[PDB]
Amino acid sequence: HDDLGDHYLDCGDLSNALKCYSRARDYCTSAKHVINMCLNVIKVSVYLQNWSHVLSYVSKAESTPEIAEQRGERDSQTQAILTKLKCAAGLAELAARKYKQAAKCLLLASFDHCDFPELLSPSNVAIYGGLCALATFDRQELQRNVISSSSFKLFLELEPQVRDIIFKFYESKYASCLKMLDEMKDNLLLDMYLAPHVRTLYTQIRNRALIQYFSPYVSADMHRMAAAFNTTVAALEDELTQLILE
Amino acid sequence: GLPHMIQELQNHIHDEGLRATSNLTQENMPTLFVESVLEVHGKFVQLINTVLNGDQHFMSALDKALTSVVNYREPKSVCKAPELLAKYCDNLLKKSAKGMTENEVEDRLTSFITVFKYIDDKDVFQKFYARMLAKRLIHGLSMSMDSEEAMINKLKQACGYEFTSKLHRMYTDMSVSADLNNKFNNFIKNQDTVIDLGISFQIYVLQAGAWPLTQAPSSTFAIPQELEKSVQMFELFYSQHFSGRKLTWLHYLCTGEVKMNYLGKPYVAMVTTYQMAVLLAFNNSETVSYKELQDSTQMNEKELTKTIKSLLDVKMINHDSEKEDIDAESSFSLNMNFSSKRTKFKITTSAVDEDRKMYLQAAIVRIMKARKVLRHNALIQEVISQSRARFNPSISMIKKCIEVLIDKQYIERSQASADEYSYV
Amino acid sequence: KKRFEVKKWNAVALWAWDIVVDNCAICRNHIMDLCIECQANQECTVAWGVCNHAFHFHCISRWLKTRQVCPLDNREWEFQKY
Amino acid sequence: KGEWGFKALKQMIKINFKLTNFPEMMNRYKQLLTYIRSAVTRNYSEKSINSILDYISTSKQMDLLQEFYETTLEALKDAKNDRLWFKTNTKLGKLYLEREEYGKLQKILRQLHQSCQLKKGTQLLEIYALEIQMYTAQKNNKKLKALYEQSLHIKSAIPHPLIMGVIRECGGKMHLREGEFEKAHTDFFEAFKNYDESGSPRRTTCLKYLVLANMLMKSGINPFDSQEAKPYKNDPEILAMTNLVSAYQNNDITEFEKILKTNHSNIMDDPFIREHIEELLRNIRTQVLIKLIKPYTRIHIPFISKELNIDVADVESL
Amino acid sequence: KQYNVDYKLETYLKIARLYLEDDDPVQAEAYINRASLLQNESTNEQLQIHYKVCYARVLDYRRKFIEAAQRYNELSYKTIVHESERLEALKHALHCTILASAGQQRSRMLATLFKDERCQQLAAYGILEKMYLDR
Ligand SMILES: [Zn+2]
Ligand SMILES: [Zn+2]
Ligand SMILES: [Zn+2]
């Protein structure tokens, strides 16, 4: 079976691989072998761009060992499998137009256990974990999951642009943050797994910023707001009209 | 059905324990008690493990029977068992000359921890073990520091950190005393002015709170003049080294060597400072009076008489007649003609309580009914605040009452957290 | 130099803090005062811990209903002495 | 032989050391070591020897000491190297770190445990503290954190209050770097307690760090209110820190800034206080702002700027 | 030497008083803090009275006016001291209450002093009665 899987990996044939996996699914004896085969089927489903099977297999893997080992065992010492499956689930959820859960299940990654540059590189992992968190996470959980998180600090310094973006957005700075977001947008569009989901994310981020800009104010100056959001007063007025309408 | 046979086997075990522990010699009693209880427990645990795949109720009843039998209180007599176990520990850890390798001692202690866990009155055993460990550490009777550390670690695992909190500090005090002595030697050696103490000085600086030793006696022992420079230099060193502390020299626990070299070279004697001040006062002449010793050593009457009796045991000084009783002459004299044979000559040798317990139990029950759920700290605080009207509670007594009410099924420990109590 | 000299002295001494406790860390009043709470509106005594830190009984009672640790050493609080 | 006999032999050892004659000294020392190990129980004679080699041996004699250390290390591996090897290792290896002892430690560590398939907590903590000291000298933050979490697994050890000082100081420093001020405070308090119990030089450095950690966790409770920290409150190296706490608690910007400016070259020079001072002068400003706006329902921003000494833009941002 | 508690208490009170006459409230408070630890175990009534007087003086010097006022007022209820000493303690309590910060504690102390029938003889009874009436 191992040689057959290797041959299917190096050949590209997937239909016979699916048939063989369906035939061999009934033959399970040890949890470790089930883990390896589940990881392989997750990889082939990612290649096939079929996320329903990814979600089903992830849910099965989590629910099999008495609800994910109850509360939780000793944190990852050398078992890098959990980071790999979390990263795969994050990619699947991000590609399924679900940014919040992708950020939630992608932020729980360790640099020491993310040394497999075959699924998602550290640079774009940090890019995704920063962009999705900025777009979907509120201030409290963004503070408690990104800035306060020391594990994600390594990812943030790996891609300094995202770290600067998050830090400036958190500290009520929007002119520089949005300018750098626009500057990095061109590189983000050249990406593969983020580009179709970039534009909407960007708008979300902007809207969040807009709301935050008016959170501590009961009367605000439109000129300063427009200067802080790198736009003219008329465009800002239209955008705020749309935001108030909804 | 089930409770009937459980009860009858419990009485059978209890009577078997009494029969095994009875008719024993009073000399080797600790060892026989420990060995008999250990062998009974091992046989019974083997019997219950080999048959019926555990059956937890059987060993639970066995543990209950052991707990009830070890706290065998004679009428008006205190429970001798914790003292017996502490004496067994001290004898095992002392430097006996009959082999007693470290591995065997460790095995004996880790087997003994099982019978130790049934004491239920562990504060008396803790105080006895602390006192005997203090004596062993001060007098150097410990055969190995590793064995003492292993015993303290075993006790900590058995009960907790708080139980072995003072013993850890005593062990660290012994560990750091050597460093303190080396630093003091460096300090006197590196002074700008030359310091000649005239005495080879070694000190054991110990924590006042951790060690059971204290200046409880009101002895007014005047310091000998020869070693005053040592105490002054070490006080200066301690002031320069540790700021904000003070030193209280235990003059009844410090010993030293006095050398005789011009009286026929009778080797060197080793005596306590109490037994050394009188010898130093004997420098004026061969015979001295009680008044001279009182004015020189400035010791209390009880301590001075104890020193005189110990000297008479040594036959260092003597009285010509039988007038050594309470009088005004007390004409002691030297007995240099009775010279030593060896060289070392190393000589080295309640109604209110029941009322308070009942009050605490009633207060705990009433508070537990009032709240129906609480934490340990909250329960202790409420009990103290309620019973402060009549007396100041002791936390050990409150915890003992909590345990005895848990055994009596008045209150129970929560399944989720062991520090939470619920009224049942 | 003398007739019966002394060679060695194995001294034993006990060290203790010059000032153990002089003010409750919570109320900032002296440990023999009225804990600042009994002072403004009324038995006030000392409550030691396993660390021997000796706060006011009422002050440590008020502190324990919110935090489970000792104010000074930030370790788990256990009552001892009263 | 006996006590006087052994003392006479040590006197002759001293006499022969005075007239050097190195080969005789080495073979005499080897024969003494072999006889001592084969006949008398080690413990007391070994502590006596350890006390002996500190009062005279410290005066220069660098090459002779190096040769003696090499010979003792080579000739003590055959029987046991547990009593004094740790302390000589810590003393000598602080400055050189000649990359050799670590290699054989790693080899024996790989050989001992995994090949066979805690009762050794004290020595494990000692070697962990030695590794922590070496990696601190090498500035390896991740390895220091890993060592601290690995040493946290030992719960059955009775170590010297200098090992528990080193590892607790490392834990406090890593907690400060990560941002967990609550854990850094207790770690630094434990480290300072252990260092004060035994030690002197590395004592008024964990007290400063404990003060900083206490001030970084919203303050409350004076650090100089415990028995341990109170005597060192007026220490010359801690006067700035106790003044900083006295200004921080019972908040006042003027006193805090004056203490900062006066001790510009005293406290904020190491990268541990200078990095964390920007968090200060902001928490105290926040507390002053909270206290100031408590009785107001409408307050002028320029009034707050005048009270807080910062300008209008910084007041609005805060 | 292990001195008796009375000797240490007397020396500490004397040092605190001497520092007070030197206008050194911080050292007086430092040496009254030591005396406060020994006052609860001594049995000398005169020593306890002297400690209470010194503590009230130290609190008054440290501008702890309400606490010093309460201490003076409770010291003026002691029958051991002479009539003149009790009247002087009451006068000091009144002065400290008048100098205290306005609040609930100060108002209660003013009411307590007003209810006292010996405050009429003091030279500040008019001020006491005008501050008691929230005038
Ligand atoms: Zn208090
Ligand atoms: Zn109170
Ligand atoms: Zn504490």
Image (cartoon, grey):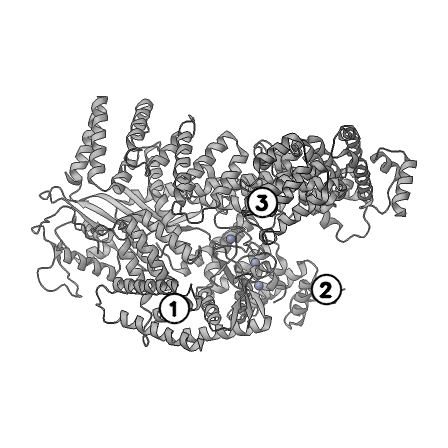
Kindly identify which chain the residue marked by label 1 belongs to. B
Q: Quadrant of residue D67?
A: top left
Kindly identify which chain the residue marked by label 3 belongs to. A
* Residue closer to the observer: B363 or A110: A110
Answer with left or right where residue D209 lies relative to residue D125. Answer: right
The quarter of the rendered structure image containing the C terminus of chain B is bottom right
* Residue closer to the observer: B363 or A201: A201
Say if B309 sits above or below A216 in the image: below
The mark lying in front, picked from 1 and 2, is 1
Q: Is residue B78 something that shows in the picture?
A: yes
**Looking at the image, which residue is at 42% across and 64% down?**
B54
The mark lying in front, picked from 3 and 2, is 3
Measure how far apart labels 1 and 2 are at the Cα level.
76 Å
Measure how far apart labels 1 and 3 are at the Cα level.
46 Å
Three-letter amino acid code at disc 2?
Answer: Met
Say if B345 sits above or below B304 in the image: above
**Residue at the spot of label 3:** A34
Say if B388 sits above or below A230 in the image: below
**Residue at the spot of label 2:** E131
* Residue closer to the observer: D286 or D137: D137
Asked whether the residues under marks 1 and 3 belong to the same chain, the reply is: no
